[PDB]
Image (cartoon, rainbow, N blue to C red):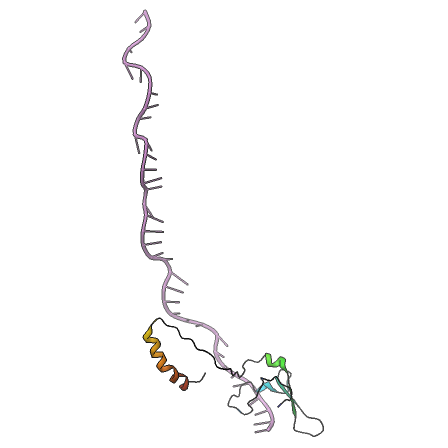
Length: 94
RNA sequence: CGCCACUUCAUGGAAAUAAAUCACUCACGAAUGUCUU
């Protein structure tokens, strides 16, 4: 973990998401750059580059509670949506 | 823990449809109804 990061910046080290593996490494385009630490060999330390953080294709975003608005002039459609909406989100990922 | 990327870049439908297609006014008015030898 680089010990200089924005307060909203967090990492999931081992995840099934294996795209964007170049975001941590050697090249200057990487968001987090690993170089061999001084003194002791191995046990490299990481540096956070905010400029590369901005130009990342995908980010893991978690928000507070947010609203979903469904509009329909058909009352029976809305009431059927109300029954199935809690089940729909439980059964699906996005 | 180390190392490492490929793939995909628009199809289907609608392509004009109805309303009004000339309306009103003037449709001849005035002079001459014989004149001069």
